[PDB]
Image 1 (tube, rainbow, N blue to C red):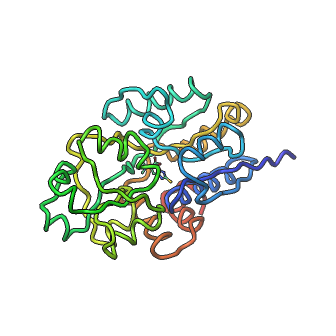
Image 2: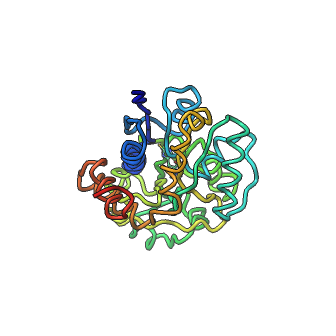
Length: 275
Ligand SMILES: C[N+](C)(C)[C@@H](Cc1c[nH]c(=S)[nH]1)C(=O)O
């Protein structure tokens, strides 16, 4: 009886798809609940509004994204990842009555990336160095990174950078930078494409980017109906290194492995999942 089915969605990319499947695997093993993973469901605003509306039940959301996009007005937060989690978790519960579980260990930050030869040619080590060459290089940014105060709007406001920006589909920006039609893109720090395409991440010297740790986001009402979801999904808390998540992304995004299988093998190897 009562085999309730949860909708777990992810933002664009292998990582949310991997994360969502880990949520499904954990949920189905340890609760009387099934789960459906919705890969590549949308961007932050869509996932967030889908959650509040009940179209989805869980998705992995990132701490700095809670503080910077989701919370309005955005609070001025530190760079301590734990403090940023607490503001996110308390802020989003007050604002929208969403429960935000404990963050995973790794950080997946927005990272301004250039090909390694571009960085050598133009002497680019930090984001500030782009001011030197903002009239020579072409940037390709996701639409969301463009519109985000911690994205390109913050490249303008904090760095003074007025880059020549073309808004890209997320999956195209990496092929553009590789083939040469753009020279700057908004990478995600754990993206396998960084290592695969000789992309060098420019250092965030003015510290525009907040901490970004992922954790399940969910209505508080769902957590009251199923309190076991907190214990169950929190076995991921403080776990998964950038190196581990990067390898998982390689497997799904580069090797074409199934995200469920990659998540499953990993949770099993970590002892987080039977067999
Ligand atoms: C984790 N991250 C890199 C800081 C972004 C990634 C992201 C934002 N929108 C989509 S789609 N992906 C986020 O989830 O906010």
